[PDB]
Length: 159
Length: 159
Ligand SMILES: COc1cc(Cc2cnc(N)nc2N)cc(OC)c1OC
Ligand SMILES: COc1cc(Cc2cnc(N)nc2N)cc(OC)c1OC
Image (cartoon, rainbow over all chains, first blue to last red):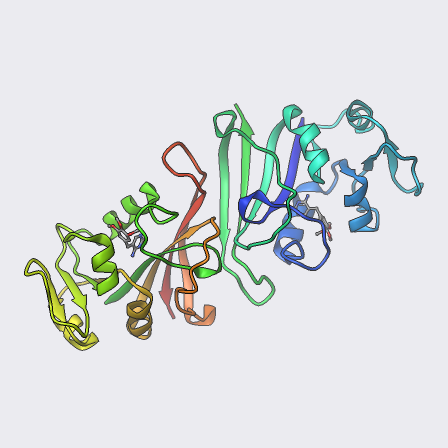
């Protein structure tokens, strides 16, 4: 099935700028934990922004432009992206905003990190209509030495 | 013992403006649940802002000015406020920022609502040094019909 995994600042803002509120080591450990040994689909900006292949995962870049790295798979369509995942229990869509948009209607599961931090972004995680989605897990953490804002992991399943 | 209970927007902003992010019915049910059959200490602005006595609780207003309502107790000092609570298991300090400030060093427990909402306030909940405080409970809720932002209840105990 298709899952989206995303880090949200307040007002559901997202961004892939390296250091920021998107550098939270705890968010990156949670990302790693929930994507290892799964295919990841990402848009080109998310690929540029991570700037290396994610090891232990098949990396699929959805882009209208031709590929510039042979260590990952490049595709032009959401159907091509899905087909390149093969027969697997779970496909992980890892951003950015355009990619989240085109995969949400097909997704059955959301892994969200609510980061208790203010960013101006103008680029938002898409509108998951609460009537369509059931929260099944949440886990709050305080700010600590490594993690300079509080955050909350949430998993939602589609009804 | 002395507890603080407070609603925080991002950056630990607080405010007592009626409708706002401080109108969250769920935050008000949680406030009621955790303060019923306890004394409440508040500053004058919090008293003006609530604009009625809280029933089922002894209401103590800490103010340098003389009292203007006989249904509540008025005092001039934190010691006077504490003494007017009598022998009770738990004293609840309900704001505002000046009152939170002068009671934090004496508090052993914090009831915080983290509201996932942006407000400009310039008036902040005080710095609870994470090394002094242990989170023992947290409970995330999604935005719903009644509650127009996600929120998280947290209880911390002093080490
Ligand atoms: C693995 O490294 C990164 C991964 C991501 C995507 C991402 C990060 N966190 C969460 N929860 N969901 C995601 N989709 C974003 C990044 O930039 C902030 C990364 O930089 C290290
Ligand atoms: C009982 O009514 C109110 C109470 C408060 C204080 C308050 C409200 N919520 C929380 N969690 N802590 C508090 N100290 C603040 C208020 O204004 C927003 C109230 O208006 C109804």
